[PDB]
Structures are given as structure tokens and as C-alpha cells.
Image (cartoon, rainbow, N blue to C red):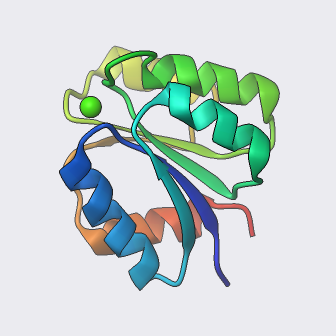
């Protein structure tokens, strides 16, 4: 029943709360703080789902998205952001993001997102 979730979030505080929720739902995860840190991990381990922040000190989530859609065509990706914008949400969906999330969102919503979108 478990999913293995890659979590990409530069905010310490939100990263830990999201990890706490994932565990609550019986889910394996790896948490990194940058898209640049996510790429080595994506080549080491298979994941059922990627959840990435959009605004990060480095490569941004839209660039990580297009990069995951290239190398891992099977991998669902959720984008989350504090600064939502309609045009960029449209572009992420057009590129095959599973969802485009404006922060914040309750822990039970994140577990429903994983169930709706993770492989398995
Ligand atoms: Ca950020």
C-alpha cells in the first residue's frame, strides 16, 4: 500500500512537516532541499511520486519538471508553490505535471494527493 515519495523542498520547516505527513500515511520517502540534489537521488532509487517546490535557490521546479518528464516518462510529478500563477499552472499541466498546488495545504490533503497520483 506504501508509495515511495521523493520530496524536494528548500524550506526546512515545510520539508519536515511534509515528511511527518508522509510517514503518517505509511509511505516511504526521501527528502532533498534542491532540484540539483534530487537528480543524483533519482538515478539511485525508483520513486512512485515526486513532489517539488517551484521556487528554489537554484534550478526551479518547472525546470526539474521538464527534466523528469524527459528522463523518467513514467514518473508522476506534483508541483507546489507559495506564489501561484495561472499561466505557469497551465504550462506545468500542459507538460504533464500531475497537479499544481498553492501552499499551504493540510496533511490529509497531501495523503489524498499521493493516493490519487502515485504509481501503485
Ligand atoms: Ca522555496
Report the residue at 39% width, 18% height from top: 88
Report the residue at 80% width, 27% height from top: 71
Q: Establish if 21 lies above or below 53.
A: below
Task: Report the side of 59 relative to 40 (left or right).
Answer: left
Q: Quadrant of residue 19?
A: bottom left
Residue 94 in view of the camera: no
Report the residue at 33% width, 62% height from top: 18
Task: Report the side of 11 relative to 99 (left or right).
Answer: left
Q: Quadrant of residue 116?
A: bottom right
Q: Establish if 39 lies above or below 94.
A: below
Q: Position of residue 78 (x, y in %)?
A: 50, 44
Q: Establish if 81 lies above or below 32.
A: above
Task: Report the side of 25 relative to 46 (left or right).
Answer: left
Residue 35 in view of the camera: yes
Quadrant for the C terminus, please.
bottom right
Q: Position of residue 73 (x, y in %)?
A: 80, 35
Callout count:
0
Q: Position of residue 46 (x, y in %)?
A: 77, 54
Report the residue at 32% width, 20% height from top: 57
Q: Position of residue 20 (x, y in %)?
A: 33, 73
Quadrant for the N terminus, please.
bottom right
Which quadrant of the figure shows ligand 1? Answer: top left
Amino acid at each position: 500500500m506504501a508509495a515511495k515519495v521523493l520530496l524536494v523542498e528548500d524550506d526546512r520547516a515545510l520539508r519536515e512537516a511534509l515528511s511527518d505527513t508522509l510517514l503518517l500515511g505509511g509511505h516511504e520517502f526521501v527528502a532533498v532541499d534542491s532540484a540539483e540534489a534530487a537528480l543524483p537521488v533519482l538515478a539511485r532509487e525508483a520513486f512512485s511520486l515526486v513532489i517539488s517546490d517551484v521556487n528554489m535557490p537554484g534550478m526551479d521546479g518547472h525546470q526539474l519538471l521538464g527534466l523528469i518528464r524527459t528522463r523518467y516518462p513514467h514518473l508522476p510529478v506534483l508541483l507546489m508553490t507559495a506564489y501561484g500563477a495561472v499561466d505557469r499552472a497551465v504550462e506545468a499541466m500542459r507538460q504533464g505535471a500531475a497537479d499544481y498546488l498553492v501552499k499551504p495545504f493540510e496533511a490529509r490533503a497531501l495523503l489524498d494527493l499521493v493516493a490519487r497520483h502515485a504509481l501503485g
